[PDB]
Length: 164
Ligand SMILES: [Cl-]
Ligand SMILES: [Cl-]
Ligand SMILES: [Zn+2]
Image 1: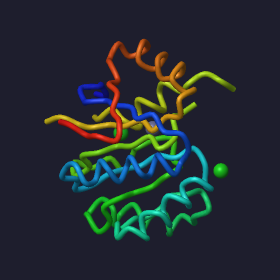
Image 2 (image 1 turned 30 degrees about the horizontal axis):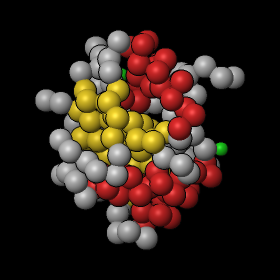
Image 3 (image 1 turned 135 degrees about the vertical axis):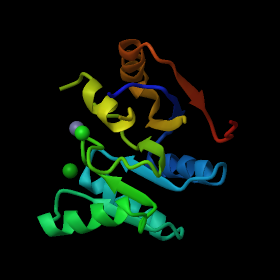
Image 4 (image 1 turned 60 degrees about the vertical axis):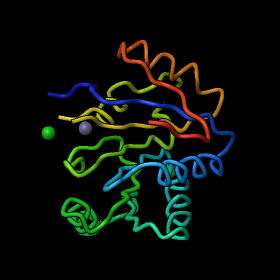
C-alpha cells in the first residue's frame, strides 16, 4: 500500500540553528495544516520544541520519556487536529500519519553507518501530492545519495529561497 508518490527535497544546513531557520522559511512559504517532524535524538527533539514554542507554533512532542497514557493523549489530540506540529523521535509514522498532514520533515536523516531505508519509507511514504524535506549537513549527502538510488526517486535541492 506504501509508495513514494510525493515531492522530496533536501536543504544543506551547517548546524541545527540553520535547520530550524530553514524550517521557518518553509512555514513562511506555503500553507501547512499539519506536519510531522522526525528527530534522531531526544535532546534534539526537545530543543526544536522550545524553539517552536518561542515562535508561536502549537507543538506536541513524542519522545520516549512518555508513559502509555501520555502517548495516548498526544497522539489522539494530533489526529483530531488539536495540535499542528508533532515532533517525534519515533522511527515510524504508523498511527499518526493522518490525512491532514501535508508536510513531513526529517530533521535528522534516519542513519552503524548505513541509512535506514524502511525507516525513511515509513516516515515519508503514505498508505493528491505530499511534501517531504530532509535537513542535512553537507557530509550527509553520501547517505542521501544512496537513499535516492535505493528508491529511484529524485530528492531535489533547496536553499534559503523556497519556490513551488
Ligand atoms: Cl536520545
Ligand atoms: Cl498500518
Ligand atoms: Zn512502522
